[PDB]
Length: 338
Ligand SMILES: [Zn+2]
Ligand SMILES: [Zn+2]
Image (tube, rainbow, N blue to C red):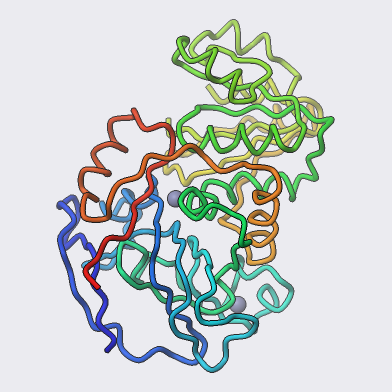
């Protein structure tokens, strides 16, 4: 009665394979969700490949989950069976440390668990998480495209909150894959002036229609230099000239890293000192911000353009992600036998 059908990597770099496991008894602090959709992004690939030397094999990935509650632990508050919720990067936190009790559960300094790190995620017919991390969806939010908001969306949304970004500010976005695409739509709803840095000069018309006010060839060194002093906030999605880009920050501006790149970034202290600039990063959101983002997306239409695959075609979906051709986020539709 606790069997979960899933897709797992048995070792690093393998094709994902059909995998059944015994989830054990649902614990009082947990909820169980029947998966409807699950987004796919490069953080899944990184865990599948043990890039961060934290993967427990077999690993069931998937951390952009939309589904409905099918079971509640006795400690769950505010939820009901049948309710549509989202589950993102974080599955459990301790609820009692200073960070958790003060509403920063993503910064938990006690025991905490990420959805796909030593835990089974959303590439499955059911998934479990702590009740505070099952984020209620507005009834009017399209479930098919909402999954990516729990990862790509929140990693852009949280720096907007933290840096108190307003419509008057000018924000730059470095690299426009699926993550840069979500950033542009969110920033357009925010009212900001938007510059997109792209190495593909052919995409200039599509980026502008996406909401970008300006498009800069990130390969042109002189063109990046010509952006000196413009940005209150610079959002990097990349994975590879940081002096040149720090120069494009306005006074008091921030360079903010979204995804976990492992390559160290050499920072000249003088470049931070002279303009009172900062380098920062932020995790994948606490429950209050996740709730706020879903509410905002129901009002503004920030959801990404998605390509939908059946979950039974996960390996094909992973190949599509790797091709770079996805426009713009890949989502799996759960299609397990009932
Ligand atoms: Zn993701
Ligand atoms: Zn905690």
